[PDB]
Image (spheres, coloured by chain):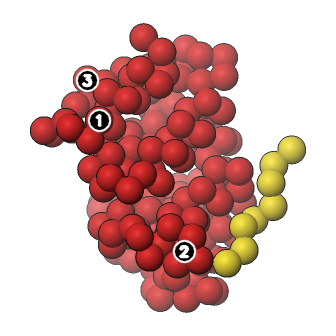
């Protein structure tokens, strides 16, 4: 349901 | 009044001082709303990413209040990357970072660090925080105000 961890 | 109504007043850039009346009003509203947590995080995320520092600062103080007043159902929302990524963007140079003040950034880091201890249950918050340190955004764990309820 949730998004994936953002990556910089 | 509505959720946005309470928050708009609790984060108004024009406020001469924090208005705890509205800050609390916002929290109570969420606790009443069936979808208060979901709506609340998205609303807060936005206010926090505001170029107006006083608006972002107040939004963070309101966020802090919510964690202490809106229980488990709020924590679950803040514990998802969907919200966590919004905070990362605020402190990461690849996004808002270079346009946001230190005061705002450190407050975010402080809260994030605080949550990894307070909410050992929310594993996604820890990953978000580590990712920050790993990328050099957080050199060392920061010092935080004394609060014996942070387990």
Sooner in the amino-acid sequence: mark 2 or mark 1: 1
Q: Where is residue B71 in the image (x, y as percent from the top left)?
A: 55, 33
The residue carrying mark 2 is B92
The residue carrying mark 1 is B12
Sooner in the amino-acid sequence: mark 3 or mark 1: 1
The residue carrying mark 3 is B21
Which of B73 and B103 lies nearest the eye of the viewer? Answer: B103
For the view shown, which residue lies furthest in the right direction? Answer: A1
The residue at the point 47 percent across, 54 percent down is: B49
For label 1, count other residues whose C-alpha is less than 10 Å away and answer few (under 14), some (14-19) or many (20+).
Answer: some
Name the quarter where the N terminus of chain B is drawn: top left
Side (left or right) of A3 relative to B70? right
Query: In this rendering, does residue B38 appear at all?
Result: yes
Side (left or right) of B100 relative to B131? left
Residue A1 falls in which quadrant of the image?
top right
Q: Are marks 3 and 2 on the same chain?
A: yes
The residue at the point 15 percent across, 39 percent down is: B17
Residue B75 falls in which quadrant of the image?
top right
Chain at numbered mark 1: B
Q: Chain A is drawn in which colour?
A: yellow
Calculate the distance from the C-alpha at mark 2 to the C-alpha at mark 1.
25 Å
**SS class of the residue under badge 1?**
loop
Residue B110 falls in which quadrant of the image?
bottom left
Calculate the distance from the C-alpha at mark 3 to the C-alpha at mark 1.
13 Å
Mark 3 or 2, closer to the camera: 2
Query: In this rendering, does residue B149 appear at all?
Result: no
Q: Position of residue B34 (x, y in %)?
A: 66, 17
Q: Tag on residue B114? A: none
């Amino acid at each position: 349901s949730d998004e994936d961890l953002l990556h910089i | 009044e509505s959720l946005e109504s309470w928050l708009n007043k609790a984060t108004n850039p024009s406020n001469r001082q924090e208005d705890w009346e509205y800050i609390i009003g916002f929290c109570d509203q969420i606790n009443k709303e069936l979808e208060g947590p979901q709506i609340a995080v998205r609303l807060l995320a936005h206010k926090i990413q505001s170029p107006q520092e006083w608006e972002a600062l107040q939004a963070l103080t309101v966020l802090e209040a919510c964690m202490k007043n809106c229980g488990r159902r709020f924590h679950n929302e803040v514990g998802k990357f969907r919200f966590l990524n919004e905070l990362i963007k605020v402190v990461s140079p690849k996004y808002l970072g270079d346009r946001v003040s230190e005061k705002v950034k450190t407050k975010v880091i402080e809260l994030l660090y605080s949550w990894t201890m307070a909410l050992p249950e929310e594993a996604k918050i820890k990953d978000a925080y580590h990712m920050l340190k790993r990328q050099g955004i957080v050199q060392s764990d920061p010092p935080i105000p004394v609060d014996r309820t942070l387990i």
